[PDB]
Image (cartoon, rainbow, N blue to C red):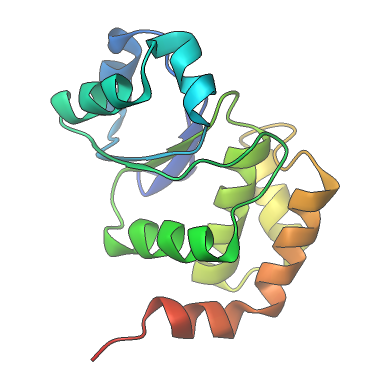
Length: 161
């Protein structure tokens, strides 16, 4: 498990045991954004809902937003992901299977939106703590798009009464 921004947001891969989840908790993790697909989760936990209850049972609030390996969230999923990540700033953990491609993409996107980083700085930032972050061209293209639509994303994320 790694932090991109000390105790505010970090990433990791799929936990194998419950002890590994308790390790997250000791690290400061409080909320978990789950990105792998049901079948990926099931490889280590048998059932997706059982995995989510385990996170909830260990005091972590989970949010499942399934993204296909090598892929990126749909625009609607990204809105949900960002509303979730921005609702509470402390102890956010984002994980996929290996915590490199998918996780790295979401993490870089977070930096872009919250710090106004240019796509390349955001990628280098994540790669410095997680080598290989942002695996595919689709993920890289997505990040440039996020920077380009930054103002629009923030506006939509905070549309309120």
